[PDB]
Amino acid sequence: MGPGFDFAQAIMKKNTVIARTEKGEFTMLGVYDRVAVIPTHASVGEIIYINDVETRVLDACALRDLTDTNLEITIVKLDRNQKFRDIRHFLPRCEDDYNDAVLSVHTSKFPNMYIPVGQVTNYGFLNLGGTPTHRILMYNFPTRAGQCGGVVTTTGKVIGIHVGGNGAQGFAAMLLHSYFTD
Image (cartoon, rainbow, N blue to C red; front, side, top):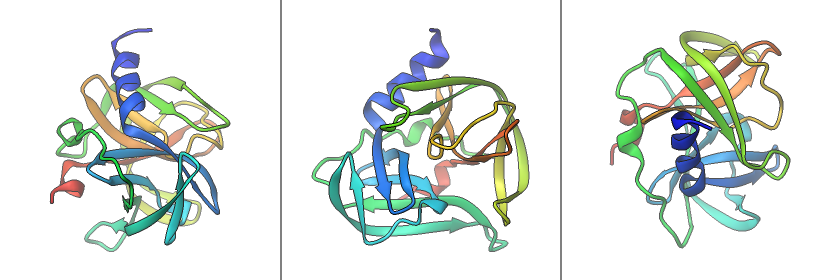
């Protein structure tokens, strides 16, 4: 509808796949080469389905901060025959608050879904499903099951992936440039 949705669509159309684990279908953001991210509660194993094709997992790393606190981001390297467009230059370098973000989801349940979520707070600590979690972004939208893995963008920036909600608010794990240096 406007330039926020423009940037979100440009990321969805080239940098997402549908990931299926034994815990469900997730929006999965591809970052560069064969490297993608997904919520850690997806419980990635040795094999994953990528757009319904059986795919070997070459590496999976559940990130934690240097306090040994959950970040709810798993970095996955896929045995895929095709690279993702490199989008690492759209990742923030530091923790921050944002205005006027969009949450974008693409699954079998919710194809081509875009939600203007508005202002994003650097929330910090969250007890997420009973797990102490850091680097949480919060937005005041009543987000639902089906949305986990959804991408949170502003114009020019890819800032997080949706990891939960409480019925009134939604919560994303931050993406930082420093997670994807090689």
